[PDB]
Amino acid sequence: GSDALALDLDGDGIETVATKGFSGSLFDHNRDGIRTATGWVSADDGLLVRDLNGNGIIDNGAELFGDNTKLADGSFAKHGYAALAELDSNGDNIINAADAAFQSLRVWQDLNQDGISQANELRTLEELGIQSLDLAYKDVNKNLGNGNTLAQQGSYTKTNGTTAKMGDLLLAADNLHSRFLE
Ligand SMILES: [Ca+2]
Ligand SMILES: [Ca+2]
Ligand SMILES: [Ca+2]
Ligand SMILES: [Ca+2]
Ligand SMILES: [Ca+2]
């Protein structure tokens, strides 16, 4: 679908726009591809991702964090942020540099908004200067404009000692195309 998890990377809130990058050709009810976006995360911010095949290649709808990812028994999550709680190794309730999954997590920033993730568009948490993520959030259910939404918001720490927002989003999309494709 179009449900997502994102980080505020430059420290002024998670922000979204209408799509214009790839939108000069739109997918249709028989042409296979990715579900047609009308809005997306603006390039100062990034999506939280993981290759579930461990080679650092994002291609499937579970590889985005969001309500279409699964928990450690194979169940879908009720809220995509809570799927991060399976990844804490020691039970301190932070995702930090001592957890194995900290190296497996990545962040995606797409400048062309084509819905495919390519290798230059990805960041590891250490290359992104992240030190920890909090497994704690509040429900905010806030509009972001252009049909986009922020459901829930938590927090993260940078290696430079700055702290910033992270959260669960709904991104704007074509409703019929989002039923022809997942
Ligand atoms: Ca921002
Ligand atoms: Ca994959
Ligand atoms: Ca959600
Ligand atoms: Ca931990
Ligand atoms: Ca791309």
Image (cartoon, rainbow, N blue to C red):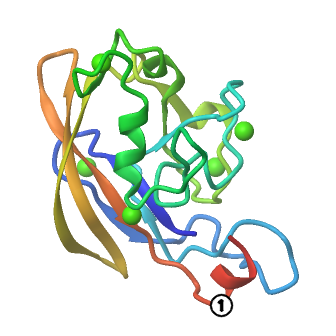
In the picture, the quarter occupied by the N terminus is: bottom right
Closer to the camera in the image, 75 or 120 = 75
Identify which residue is drawn at 68% across, 25% down. 54
Above-or-below relation of 82 to 140? above
Residue 160 in the image: state x and y as whole percent.
Answer: 17, 16
Amino acid type shown at disc 1? Leu
Residue shown at 12% from the left, 26% from the top = 162
Q: Mark 1 highlights which residue?
A: 176
| Residue 142, image quadrant | bottom left
Residue 56 lies in quadrant: top right
Total numbered labels placed on residues in the image: 1
Picture coordinates of residue 148, whole percent (x, y): 36, 74
Q: Residues within 10 Å of mark 1 (few under 14, many from 20)?
A: few
Towards the viewer: 164 or 77? 77
**x, y percentage for residue 122?**
55, 33
Q: Is residue 73 left or right of 167 when viewed as pictured?
A: right
Q: Is residue 46 above or below residue 15?
A: above
Q: Quadrant of the C terminus?
A: bottom right
Check the image and name the residue furthest to the front: 73
**As drawn, 141 above or below 43:** below
Looking at the rendered structure, the secondary structure element under dot 1 is: loop
Ligand 3 within 8 angstroms of badge 1 C-beta: no
Left or right of 32 on screen, residue 92: left
Question: Residue visible at 54% across and 71% down?
Answer: 20
Query: Ligand 4 is located in which of the four quadrants?
Result: top left
Give whichever of 37, 111 is nearer the camera. 37
Identify the residue at horizontal 68%, vertical 84% (top origin). 179
Q: Position of residue 125 (x, y in %)?
A: 40, 23
Side (left or right) of 131 relative to 76 = left
